[PDB]
Length: 293
Ligand SMILES: [Ca+2]
Ligand SMILES: [Cl-]
Image 1 (tube, protein in one colour):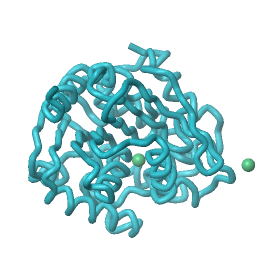
Image 2: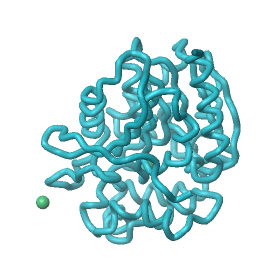
Image 3: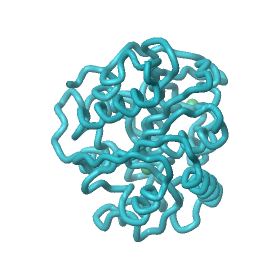
Image 4: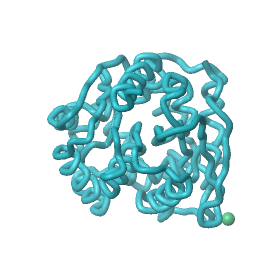
């Protein structure tokens, strides 16, 4: 299905509208997307969890239906800034102390870090295709390595701001099946305008903690990595075959984490588009185990 889940609501955070879905009552279950998606990514997964809590999915600043930052440029949309907006949004949504996080891609970096800073508020973490630790160049898939190194160079502006490569190539290229015209449309929407409307999709791969740089994200991911491998918080690892980002060393490291159940589903990076029913079912079962009634 191409239909979004829920109705978008909006909240002004530091003078900017942020968009989010919030359905149901009870302890929250937060779904957090990464690059270059939005809450739309979760549309066929969130229904599986209906009645198990308050289902929330936020659009990160500059993505989905949330506002762009003004002014925009190469210093905007770094990890730190996204973190500031999302922290403040999660505050304003009145989440309580029994939060289940469901995370993907940069959503995992954000969610893992937040969970670390608020560990007594977290009831469970489900993650998939996540940035679970700092990596090296060799840990990127062979076929995508050189393109990501290009984004991280001066060639990135032309590739992403003019040609929109992250949306038009990386996104479809990391989904096993072809998207319908309506599904592409929804992912394209926030990035139709060339220029700074696309800055978020370029700023993100420039934040990837690769070979020690950028150093502040390295250190954040190094901190949450250590913590997660030592945390008794229950965890659901949704492993993808063949996967993309959570493979190799990162996958071995994730499997060392305590109090973790694991399932494996078909997919590359955007696995929600390939096996949404398996993922949704597993998340639901996980949340049911943590919230017997
Ligand atoms: Ca302007
Ligand atoms: Cl990225």
